[PDB]
Length: 94
Length: 94
Image (cartoon, rainbow over all chains, first blue to last red; front, side):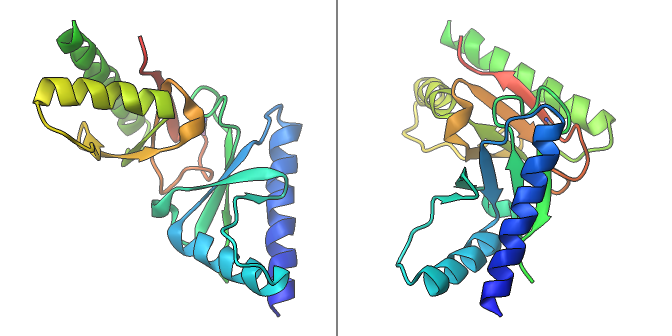
């Protein structure tokens, strides 16, 4: 069920956002692999019945990092590389 | 001296690459902010007397994450978001 897939993905992003916030981070961006982005884009085109492109999800900004493949990484971009733990990975593709 | 600036930047990237390798990571990508990328691009156009665009530095792949501003972040993209410490930030702009 593509609706279930969208509910799952929104739920996992929210969970990683919450995990980061609890640690003192401010999640601002989610990096998507090429395959991950295509997967979510297809889902949102189908579900929203809109053409895209899609630039935000879960109140944060989508940016592409092609090499992440079927995964995405929620980050606090202000402290990424200065404080360990500023990144949380999730698997987007089935 | 723009040559000195290039020597500095290559030296800082190498240092963060080495720091990551010593920790067990495999640095594969360096994320550049918009201002950081422009700065390095201008330097390399001047020094290499080539037009660009520039896609690799220090044996790793350049990818843009616009929001990093005048900074760049060396990452191990395979474990980013799974193991803390997979990212090291550097300040590119003067």
